[PDB]
Every structure is written in C-alpha cells, then in structure tokens.
Image (cartoon, rainbow, N blue to C red; front, side, top):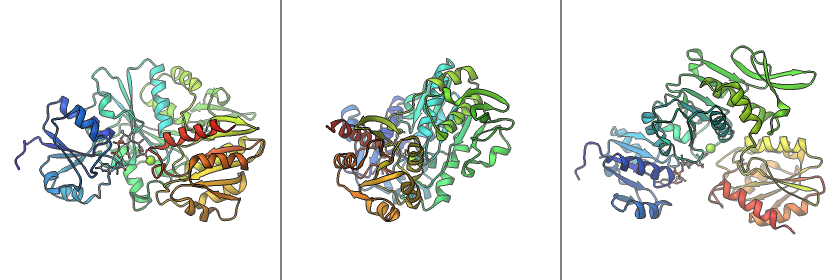
Length: 446
Ligand SMILES: CC(=O)N[C@H]1[C@@H](OP(=O)(O)OP(=O)(O)OC[C@H]2O[C@@H](n3ccc(=O)[nH]c3=O)[C@H](O)[C@@H]2O)O[C@H](CO)[C@@H](O)[C@@H]1O[C@H](C)C(=O)N[C@@H](C)C(=O)O
Ligand SMILES: [Mg+2]
C-alpha cells in the first residue's frame, strides 16, 4: 500500500470537504477522500465532478489514514473519533480547511468566533470593508468555505470561525481576532466549559491584535497584554475602547471620548445589537477601515435572516423567526429583547436537539414574558422539565402544528417567537430551513 510522500486525505465529504477537494485538485496534489457514512451528502457531487478521486465511505480504516502526511478533517466530525486519535498518535497532522487557509492566505485575516453573534458581526465587518472600498472576501463557518475565497488580489479576509474549526487550526496568525462571547453550547462535543473555551481561544494563536468583550471574561486572551487590544462594551469607554456615551438619556456609539453615532440612527435595535456594532467597529478600526465608511455601513445594516426577523402580523399578533437561536444564551436574549418591546406577551416556540444544554436559565424569562410555550423536537421534555409550571406548555410534533397552535394561544398585542434554544438537526437540514418552514407555516395561517 505505497503512497506519494505528499499524500493527504480529506476526512469528511460535506461542504468543506468539497472545498478541500477543489483546492488539492487544483494544485495537482495526491489525495483521497474518506467519510464515516456510507452515503455522505456530497458523495453524489464528488462522483459527478471528480470521478477519478479515490473515495472510501464507511468505518474509517486507521491504517489508511496513517499513510497520509496530514488529514483535513470536517469540523463536524469529532476529533475523538478513534481512527483520528490513532492517526494523531502516529504523528499524522490533524488539520482542516481553516488551518490550511491560514497557511496559504496572503492578506490580513479578521477572525471572529463566539457562541453567538459571530455571523452578524462577520457580515457587518464585511460590509464595512466593502464600504471602505477594500477588496474583501468574507466566509468560513458563515457559509462560503474559506479555501474558495483565496485569491492573490484580496486585500482583507473576514472569517467567521467555529470552535470546531479552531480545534484543528495550529496557528491562525490572524491580523485581529475576537471571541465575541462564550455561553454554554456544543456540550454534545465538549466535556465541559473548559475544553470549549480552550478551543475558541485557539483563535488567538499568533494573533497580531485582539478585540475583547469587556462584559465577558471568557473572551479575554493572555496575549491582550502583549499585542494591541481593543475592547468593546456598553459602558462608557476608556482609552483604546469602544462603548456608549450617554448624555441626557441619549446614547451614542463611541470610541474613547468621541461620540461616533447616536444609537437611534442604527436600523438594528437593543443592547445586543449595540454591542455587535461596537465589536464590528473595533475589528474594522484594527485593520484600518475609516470611521466614516464603517459608520455608513452600520447605518445601512439591516440584520440577517432568521435573527428575530419579523414575518407577519395577523389579528394583532406579530410572528418572529429567530431560528438562529440554537443555544440558551440566544433564546434568552430574544425573549428578553422582544418581550420588552411588545405591547403584549410572548408565545415561544422552542425545542429540537438541545446538545446536552442546561435549560434552567430559560425559566425566569419565560415566567416574566411568556403567555405560553410550544415545545417540539427531541429534547422538548428536557425543556419542559426546566420550565416547570411557569406558564402553560403545549407539546406538538411538527413545526406546522407548532405555528397553528401558537396562533391559537396568542392574543392581540402578543408576539409568536421561534427562538428554539436548540439545534435544528433532529428534524431539519439546518436552522435556515427551520426558519423558512416556520415562515411558510406562518404565511399559511388564514
Ligand atoms: C457542522 C459544521 O461544522 N458545519 C460546517 C461545515 O459544513 P460541512 O458541510 O463541511 O459539515 P461537516 O463538517 O461535514 O459536518 C456535517 C455533519 O457531517 C457529519 N460527518 C462528517 C464527516 C464524516 O466523516 N462523518 C460524519 O458523520 C458530522 O458529524 C456532522 O454531523 O463547513 C461549512 C463551511 O466552513 C460551515 O458553514 C458549516 O457550518 C454550519 C453553518 C454549522 O452548523 N456550523 C456549526 C459548527 C455551528 O455554527 O455551530
Ligand atoms: Mg455553534
């Protein structure tokens, strides 16, 4: 079983695996593809587009993996998979598409992770860079695989990174890096908060600057003492800091003692979105984006689909798609934020794959803001146990039923909120499909 000394193996045939196939094939390197599943989602794609690439589907063959110089592992595949552990112990480098991107990119990287907000802040910094007339490429976990962004004329890369991707990134060497926030998530993969936190802090390896959340200690890296450190927060900022300046009850986004923009001139609203705006300003300022360009993009920014997104108002009841809420921290923010905005109470739709999360933090906000909760999905029962008898709970089987029942529970002035605190993967392809099907059911109400 001979192989070339450059031989490498792509482990996982999903979207990032296909970006690795494209990259390695373009460089004419010897490689093969494996996947633990008999019928991975991009198998048909690989067979149609790369009929000559060796592909092995099923139980991983550790002896085959051990013949490669490096494995590029799908971020969704746990590195505790036994054959990967065995290859690692025999000195095979465990890598991945972000690790490879970091080793190849020829322009500064803005690297953004966090338990929440990383897609919004990544998108915003990208729009700031476009407004600053930079040749920018934006992607990563956000959707466009990072390797597909590579081009020599790119002046700035903006990457959303997951804790999973970061586990195989040896030395990202970002120009500026941030962990926006950390709250319990992905506890079906990590043993606890310590390993989850450590994985995210790999974003700082080699970072030339950092952006830190003054309100979240799990975002503060050791290197904040040795590289330029820009902080954001909602309190009044000090030197080198972004924050809010308040005068006669009017709030301004601010850098040090300079008022930048009244928060009322943003389209996005609420404390979490102000924090996101300040984080994006800090990241953009770190890579030289002019303030006037950044503020113009901030004023124009409308937010992302499935982020507490208004769908419909029917019989005085408004319907909001917050399907992006796949952890408790996100649902907490939406319940508090929308609950405080409306002239009524919430009917919350929640449940799905809870990833081993503690749901106890939902109880008090649900008791304060909800008229009822509609629960679906694999871990509906765990959520119901955490909520107790705070409010009426209605158990349903499908999202269409959940919407029909929520309409019946709601009264004029209420809002129906899909903010599930769970992954969608037990019942849906992804959280975007979950949100699209919620919006479809809402639109089908008579
Ligand atoms: C799960 C994950 O990390 N997905 C990211 C990945 O998409 P990709 O299609 O390559 O997925 P993947 O890494 O193959 O994982 C998908 C699923 O396949 C399974 N899988 C994968 C390989 C394999 O051999 N066997 C197997 O069972 C994984 O366990 C997982 O359940 O690469 C894309 C490009 O970088 C990302 O946009 C996408 O992020 C999505 C948005 C996501 O859900 N990310 C998670 C981490 C999140 O945000 O929490
Ligand atoms: Mg995640």
